[PDB]
Amino acid sequence: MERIKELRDLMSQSRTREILTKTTVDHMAIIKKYTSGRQEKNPALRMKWMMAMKYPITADKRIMEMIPERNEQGQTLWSKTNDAGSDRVMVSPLAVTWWNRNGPTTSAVHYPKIYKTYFEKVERLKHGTFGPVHFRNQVKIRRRVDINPGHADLSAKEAQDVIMEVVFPNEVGARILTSESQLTITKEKKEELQDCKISPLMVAYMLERELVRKTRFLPVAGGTSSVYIEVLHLTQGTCWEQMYTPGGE
Amino acid sequence: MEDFVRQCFNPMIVELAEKAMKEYGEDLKIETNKFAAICTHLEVCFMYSDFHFINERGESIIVESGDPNALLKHRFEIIEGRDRTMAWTVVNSICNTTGAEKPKFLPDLYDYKENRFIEIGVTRREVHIYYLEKANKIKSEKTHIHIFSFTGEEMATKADYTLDEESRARIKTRLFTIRQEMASRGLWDSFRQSERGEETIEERFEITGTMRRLADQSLPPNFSSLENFRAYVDGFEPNGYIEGKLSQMSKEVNARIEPFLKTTPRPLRLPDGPPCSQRSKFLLMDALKLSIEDPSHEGEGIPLYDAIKCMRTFFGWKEPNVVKPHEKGINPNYLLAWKQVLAELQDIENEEKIPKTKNMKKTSQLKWALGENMAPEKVDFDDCKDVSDLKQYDSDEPELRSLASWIQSEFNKACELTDSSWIELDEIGEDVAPIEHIASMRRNYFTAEVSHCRATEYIMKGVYINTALLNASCAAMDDFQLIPMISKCRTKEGRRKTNLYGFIIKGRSHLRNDTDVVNFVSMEFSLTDPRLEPHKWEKYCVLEIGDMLLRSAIGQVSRPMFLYVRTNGTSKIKMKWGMEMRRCLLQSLQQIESMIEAESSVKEKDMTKEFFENKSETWPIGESPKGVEEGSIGKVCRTLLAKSVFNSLYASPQLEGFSAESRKLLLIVQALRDNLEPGTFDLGGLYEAIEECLINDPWVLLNASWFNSFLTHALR
Amino acid sequence: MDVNPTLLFLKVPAQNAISTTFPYTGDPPYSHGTGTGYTMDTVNRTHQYSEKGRWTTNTETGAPQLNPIDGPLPEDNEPSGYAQTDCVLEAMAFLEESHPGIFENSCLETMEVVQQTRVDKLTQGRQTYDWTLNRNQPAATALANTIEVFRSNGLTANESGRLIDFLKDVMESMDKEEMEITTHFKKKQRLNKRSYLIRALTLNTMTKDAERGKLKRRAIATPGMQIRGFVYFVETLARSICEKLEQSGLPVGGNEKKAKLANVVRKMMTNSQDTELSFTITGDNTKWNENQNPRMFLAMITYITRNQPEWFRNVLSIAPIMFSNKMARLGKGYMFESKSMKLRTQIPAEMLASIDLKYFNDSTRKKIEKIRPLLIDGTASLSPGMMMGMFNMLSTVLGVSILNLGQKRYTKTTYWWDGLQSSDDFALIVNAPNHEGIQAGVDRFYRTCKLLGINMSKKKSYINRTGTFEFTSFFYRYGFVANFSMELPSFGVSGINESADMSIGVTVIKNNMINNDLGPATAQMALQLFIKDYRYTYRCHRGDTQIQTRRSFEIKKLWEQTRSKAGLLVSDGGPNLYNIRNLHIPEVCLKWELMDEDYQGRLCNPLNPFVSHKEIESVNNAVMMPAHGPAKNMEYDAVATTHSWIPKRNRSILNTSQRGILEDEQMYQKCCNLFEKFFPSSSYRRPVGISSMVEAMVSRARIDARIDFESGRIKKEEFAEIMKICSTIEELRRQ
Amino acid sequence: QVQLQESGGGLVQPRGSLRLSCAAYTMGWYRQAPLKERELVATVNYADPVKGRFTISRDNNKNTEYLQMSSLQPEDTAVYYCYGQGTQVTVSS
RNA sequence: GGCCUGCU
RNA sequence: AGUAGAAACAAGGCC
């Protein structure tokens, strides 16, 4: 109901009507990236400079109807002045902390299921067992190794169709996945995330990260396993070796 | 033939078919019979779908015209007449909502009663072959298929015909209308067989017009056209042309190697001129501290109250008077500014609660001291052209200045220990691995070594001052603000303590660019008389403000106590980089830990404890008139920390240029000392490159003097 | 006793303590005003290194151009751009012979990419010079403006959605009598043929800031949008070629560079017997970009693309053809001050052609006098050579050809050489039975380099015995030695947001521990200092302290409200549990089991009004410009929390005549959000097609209402309402 | 003897004149200014700073090149070499 | 005096 | 004045 209604409201005004009519689907990306905002050259300097202002961050308009304009002593939490090229409003950082102490609460039980990679890292490290540190010269030789320890033996494009069919089943188009490994992955990640309401985009991004294999060139000495490379900073050094066995093994 | 589609069919269908024509990118002028055939297919699709509605029952309600109501459901909903992306969108949506099977090709319609697809195709040939043809094109299909053909016959599997027969009479009447209208036209010489499935195209990227002429002007000197040059390139083969030109080329074009020996390198020449002055934003070696011995932590507390309490701890105030003038400004303004600061500090002391941040009055004194309303007003060139004085901004090499001995002593005392701990580090996760325990022990050793160091005190001073200045500039852009220089340490006894070096008055700070300058005036207490090294205080105005009595065995000194007052400035980039001075600790201690690890790779054991306690091994860390002096690892730590701190304090382009062009020569000298037969192509050029970076910066000149001393001691 | 750190090198070798010689703890040098002086100096220097060439006047642009190719051979060691066509063609032929099938294959993959590439690939770029407004703007904005102008002028082939079609339209625009542009102050202005040619062939010049390692500032250039597609295709070909060359090091990272350097040094020295001596030259090329003539790149590519479809050759040749006629905008201008009348003025650079020279100093006066003859419509012709490393990969190809030309099969002498080339820098290992052989080999290598327009910087180069050398701030001494002073500037708060900054800092510490041999205790100290700076920057202190800030009240109440305070994030004033073992774990997941369910739910709430995600590309990618290197992107692990807000934008557009761009931004974003709600996959996979917005949106409304009734919330009343509302918007679009 | 021996230098007031001789193919007179490099002055062709002031000549029987210096300036204050010991020329008031 | 902006 | 260094800041524009 609503969606077509703001569609009609947009088409009511002449300029947006023209934009909707003359613009083709292919140009979607271009106009979506059409912005006057330059990409910052020195982000640290301005982050250290903007945070000294009042209302340094930006938030959706809806914040004006969930968080009061001021806190107990009267420190303002949000302003009604919109951003430069968006309908979002500039708000103070307190509106963040306020949201974490009296804002609406939900059931975050499914975030562990979504962010599978990070929670698997935590579980692997929690059950790890350290050993003695041995001091001897390490011959670090540079090798190509896979960093992602949960890659399902799929490439970027190869798993992209799987990700769409898992999250966006209707926009798949011609592709119907042939490999049965992809079939089982789709089934599992479909039944697992059937009602998760985090965001389609973040779900797709994390599925891409988990399933897609990624490789990088690093100086290693021993190890060479996927689980042993994520902790390469902790097990191998310039003149010391720290024996380690992740919780998985 | 196109006249037929001009005449009969309605607009809607003809533009739908024209967009379907554009879909796959073939042109309509070459073969139009496909257009007519598929537009008739689309027409039968409509005429078969429309006029057919359903209500909550099955048994579709058929109405010649949809009456105004909510009961406008369509019996058959069309697939084609849409783009491939949307056709597959509808296919997938129907499959996911109806729980049916996904076909591999494009259907034409969907129906509810039987909950499935219809692929309508009316071909010229008779049905009973085209049907099974498209059937074997589609794999294991449950979608029912139904086709007509011009003779008027119908067929389908399951003997199934999904709706009214009068509609099918409609279809075949439409069909024979088409047929015996072409009869008047006469198209069957090709109508039965006009499409054979042609798909081919050649990509054409032709250079022509102006862009061709440009191609004719981007060739070697003796070529006339891109065609000729490409023909020559294709016909070109290697026939020893590099050798001919190498032989013909003059022999003066050479890269002769000049041997680099011990007697080759000469000392770097330093610029000559007036002595070098002080550039720091605060006093480093001549600072004085007024303290309260409070239990508050670094960030804990309120600045103004702490400053006032510290200043009340000192007795012996005198009416201030000029001792050493600025030599270029109006010292009475500095005097009046100091008295104004004192008066307003008392004014705060009187009232109820000390404000967290105070704003000062904009008197003419600080208007001059902070450089207010001095930027020339911006105008247009068309209005100022006849002014003779109008010229460019002064753009020339900076003034030349010779090195002085004060920077050496300042660095010397910047590496000395102190009676306080100037670093209170944060918390880290409790160490769980033995390597983490080793790291923590190493870190504790280095913290014990460097915390009691003037370099750490300078780091904290700079970080706090720049943080406060940046925050005040970003908050109080318009109005002058008072900020007391505060630094909190911990005594040997363990009691925490605060220290007040002085005050900073920040001025207008409407900083847009990263290079825009915010001006402030800094006042700092000290005991060092400025009458002994005046050239180091060229830009300072120094007053006499009191007398101090520090307990000494020579009765009690009752020394004078002066106020160094100056106008300084910074910028957003400078403030940001000065508030990250704590990475000097990193740089230094990373270097020391690299030393320790490299040495421990030799002996298979951690070597930190004996390095820091036994102090047997020592590194050359300075030269005395007797000779080169070596110090323990802790002294090396402090020296490197001081070097990094001074790099962060006296940073400038001269420093970067000299560092690079002297690292080159240092590598060459190291190669010489390693017996690697080093050689150079133009050493004089490298020397000139190094010597052009030394202009007026005390730090870079001191580094150059150190480099000359290292060369003198090396090469032996 | 006087302390002197440099004397430390008398006991510790120079490379083992080279980190001390990198003053990367202070503010790097920045430029303050115009870059016009540097642009003029660079143009004059590029034109006078090729003075002995031949002059011509382009019949299209009417600008003077200097062709030095096949010019007189140099007779001195000064820089020279007199490259010889036959010599370079022979070098490329030998490169092909030593690597058969390189050019044909690379051309095949490049042809595939060019004929399947899309227009949107041009949006994935940083600032570009929009000619519609004569100023630098984001790549997407400039592309959109150029497409709009083309469509308004009648060039609508780009509607095919293919980059090749966009380039076809671009070339067709060159043959138009009169184009039209829009300006706001809206006014429609007409550009004739020559003016549009110069506007499409021009470059925008700026001054490079944050450049560490030199006393003087330099100038850099940014091209337009008409020429970026050809550049993209040419660089794709060059990258595909260099990926097949082991002597190149430009298309790889740092660790790969080190590995290849070690391999080449071991190969050269190990194969050398006791009789052969080995020497390493640590060479830098003076005026690398100013001496590379685009015509020679045209020759190299036309030799590479031999026996290939003519359209491929044409599309790959268009780029150097435009660079050979490239123009450069002088810059911002010059600012004058009058102290007698106490005023300042800013004259644009376009007046340099006619403005009197009384206001300029001697140096600038002479520079303007020398560059004036080349001024055409406020921009200077820069035909002789490249401006700033636009063809990095082709230059690397030429250098690799030079390196391979001494494989001992072409030297025809006992001496031989090899090494590694990365544009403007190289390491050359030369072996020969005697010092005379080494001298002859280096002399011939230098001479051959001078025949290709490449000069070796004698002042910044030195030769020693193999085993010790330098390459791009990587010091090799019997094995590469860590520096850690190049990455020091990256140890602070990045400046993206709270969660992003935390993750980026911990990940940077981890990486520098893995690669740059950062010590354990040093890493712990870095973690402590980073946490301190992070808390002091975001006003998020431990909460149990009495540090009054603008955010210390809410943080303190959250602290007192929470029961398990160990689960609070550092952003919310909680303890830091990070350590050397936890540097690879996001903060949210490390504290997940310690958080209270109420705070956990409030933190990670999808409905939070702070989190905003635009595209799959910008989810967890942060662009950090590394010190002493080109802009780079990093993947940082982070959980989408309420702290993932995006900061405020500039907001200064409101005072400029270009104020309508914000309204267009808002309307485009509203339409894009509506489309995304209609097409959820719009962000992850960019939609493709040739239909218009409203068609897809209305038709999908039809179908989705239908099916969501066939099972879902919709009702007949609502379904029919949607159907007739779709009809209403249909008839509205009709009129 | 040695291989090269320059002679005839000295102190001269600006505008003054001097004749340098050298006892040693095409030969050239070079000068090295204090702090600066060894630069070509003339050969037997003249450098632009020299122009119509200095005149190089040679006696092929006596194996010697000569440099006649006229209208001398403080920029010619340098050690002059042929190609030795060199000969110091200093122009001053 | 009143109001706008701080990488456009 | 001061910052800074091959050109700039020492607020800008709009009424």
Image: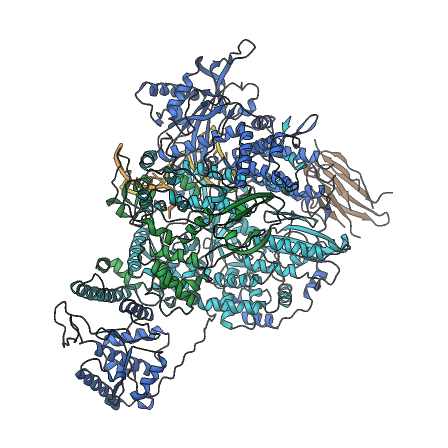
Chain colours: A green, B blue, C cyan, D brown, E orange, F yellow
In the rendered image, residue C156, in percent from the top left (x then y), is placed at 36, 67
Residue B68 visible in the current orientation:
yes
Q: Quadrant of the N terminus of chain D?
A: top right
Residue C350 visible in the current orientation:
no
Left or right, B51 with respect to B354, comes to left
Q: Is residue C415 above or below residue B415?
A: below
Q: Is residue B137 above or below residue C209?
A: below
Q: Nearer the viewer, residue B166 or C21?
A: B166
Q: Nearer the viewer, residue C451 or C166?
A: C166
Q: Quadrant of the C terminus of chain D?
A: top right
Q: Is residue C115 above or below residue A6?
A: below
Instruction: State the count of labels.
Output: 0
Left or right, A1 with respect to D86, comes to left
Q: Nearer the viewer, residue C639 or C349?
A: C639
Locate residue B438: give its quadrant: top right
Q: Residue furthest left?
A: B68
In the rendered image, residue C13, in percent from the top left (x then y), is placed at 66, 40
Left or right, C670 with respect to D24, comes to left
In the rendered image, residue B538, in percent from the top left (x then y), is placed at 53, 25
Left or right, C718 with respect to C420, comes to left
In the rendered image, residue B78, in percent from the top left (x then y), is placed at 25, 73
Q: Nearer the viewer, residue C217 or A166?
A: A166
Q: Residue furthest top?
A: B555
Q: Is residue B254 above or below residue B544?
A: below
